[PDB]
Image (spheres, rainbow, N blue to C red):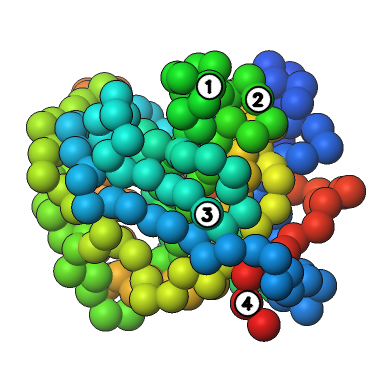
Amino acid sequence: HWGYGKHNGPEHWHKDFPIAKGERQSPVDIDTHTAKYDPSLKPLSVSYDQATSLRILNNGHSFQVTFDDSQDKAVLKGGPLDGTYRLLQFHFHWGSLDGQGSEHTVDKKKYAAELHLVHWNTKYGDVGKAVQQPDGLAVLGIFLKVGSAKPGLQKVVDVLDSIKTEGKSADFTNFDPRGLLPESLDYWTYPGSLTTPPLAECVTWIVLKEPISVSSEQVLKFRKLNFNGEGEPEELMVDNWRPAQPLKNRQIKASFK
Ligand SMILES: [N]S(=O)(=O)[C][C][C][C]C1234B567B89%10B%11%12%13B85%14B%1158B%12%11%15B%139%12B%1061B%12%112C5%153B%14874
Ligand SMILES: [Zn+2]
């Protein structure tokens, strides 16, 4: 199966998922001087007050927090989007050291980690149908840098020992994802793909300019996770990021001047 190692990592994925070499793959480097300010872009509408978290899961590639997406409770609208997108889950990508871990880069800068809040378009009715459409998903990406602790992340941090290895899940109710957001909703946007198999070209990316700060202790707990299942040879879940892919025939737009 696919992973992030030498023999199964990103350079291999195209064999099982040939769209890996497609025309709208993610992530990309965001060249800040080339991105064009688009005054037609709307403010992003992030409506998370009725979010209902369910479970936290280690799936062997990241950890994720899953939400009830059976009604319009935690939705993304506006910005570059037409219609309403329901929050399904969030997860992270991170490095072995603080100088790598993000998927998107900004003028070639890599952040220590990247948070992805994954949403799907309710007009396609379910996420499996949405992933087959060019406007099916909207992923909100937020960079993490290491400095001061993010208080809203601590509840996540402190349960990671209970999902150390692949397979493992736990109850994770009453988690408020508003506590993971930076002050500003200024963003870059472009059409792209899932950054993990199946690499489907179904995503409107919305990448926030302002990173959140997390502490060294917080990210160190991410790195204590394992890619492997319980009792198997221990391989730290680190460097679970896909590198930047060719931009090709795409424009990155900025919501801000
Ligand atoms: N890193 S990322 O945010 O680009 C990928 C998000 C993958 C989200 C999924 B799509 B398929 B299935 B549908 B449902 B399951 B599988 B992939 B994951 C979820 B949706
Ligand atoms: Zn992701």
Give the CA separation, mark 3 to mark 1.
18 Å
* Mark sitting earlier along the chain (2/3): 3
**Residue sitting nearer the eye, 191 or 70:** 70
Give the CA separation, mark 4 to mark 3.
15 Å
Mark 4: amino acid: Phe
Give the CA separation, mark 2 to mark 3.
19 Å
Mark 1: amino acid: Tyr
User: Is the shortest distance between ligand 1 and the CB of mark 1 under 8 Å?
Assistant: no
* Mark sitting earlier along the chain (1/2): 1
**Residue sitting nearer the eye, 111 or 180:** 180
Q: What residue sits 65% from the left and 57% below the top?
A: 189
Residue 61 percent across, percent down from the top left: 42, 34
The quarter of the picture where the C terminus appears is: bottom right
Give the CA separation, mark 1 to mark 2.
8 Å
Which secondary structure lies at badge 3? Answer: strand
Q: Is residue 83 left or right of residue 108?
A: left
**Residue sitting nearer the eye, 146 or 5:** 146
Q: Is residue 9 left or right of residue 90?
A: right
Is any part of residue 112 visible from this angle?
A: no
